[PDB]
Length: 397
Ligand SMILES: [Ca+2]
Ligand SMILES: [Ca+2]
Ligand SMILES: [Ca+2]
Ligand SMILES: [Ca+2]
Ligand code: NA
Image (cartoon, rainbow, N blue to C red):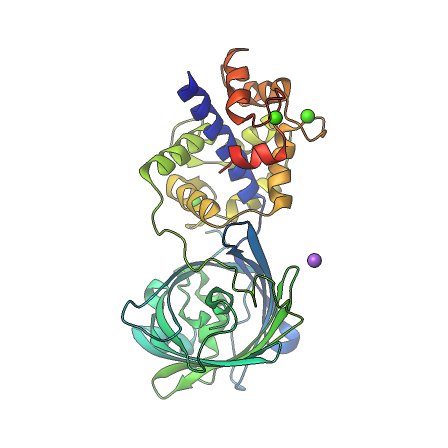
């Protein structure tokens, strides 16, 4: 009864959420910058806020070769990055342990500098920072293995306490370790600039707060890949998320079997032929039943956003990965309102039973005019017989 309702809901909410993810740009987007003989990159990072929503950090980036040698200017593509932050239980100093996995994708189905990345390469990181006049240094060390896009670093704040959250420095503190697939080796700018290296420059805008400006030199010093950085931060709020340390350090590396099974149920609403992959046709069917009407091109681009193997379809594991990440890094209010907007057909700020029934039956759920009410009940905080925004928020967690 309650069970069925709760279950029928998760499936819908998850499907809507999947469309939200597929309509978003969460990767690192790289483009050639012929005028500078380099590349540009653009992306955003989500920083979960302790007991709250999410902090956005909008990154603009340029990389320029230090040397005169030829480099590879890529076609447009992306890097997909997975990071984990941890603490060294024996470390007394303010520190961060970082693991990253970085892979290039985005282009559907080898430079001299790449030979320097065939095995495990030692890394040294040095940063000097100044944020609102609060100065600091970080040293880090570790190793990278481009064969797997793997890197592991440990950083120490050598000046005492870091005056900003460690997660805000992850992107600043070696994309040369990215795994490029065989068909995309001609688009690896980073390794092509080695050993002489490149300059990596960023402006990072933390929404509703200040911005970082960074300049780094990434180059070999003997056998070690070194990342030397300068960071300047201005316009930060003294009691904002950054200077006020209001950001979460790490997420459970967890995700229960029950959450995974919920993802699988949602997957199966898109994979209508049961073949274990989602096609543009399947994707378009679901979107249209939700009242959208994307073109073929939009459908291919939505799939391409999460298509790890470049086959043109969202395979079962690609979808699982995408959902896991959508649940770990929180949504903006604008994104939750878009999702709400799918159900709220008249746009009055209230999901009626008639609206919900419309959405469900459109998605091809066989539900009773009683199961429909049963669903509203579960979500209805204030007992008005409808679902408002704050109530939707709850229904989506
Ligand atoms: Ca299928
Ligand atoms: Ca695929
Ligand atoms: Ca409405
Ligand atoms: Ca209500
Ligand atoms: Na603001």
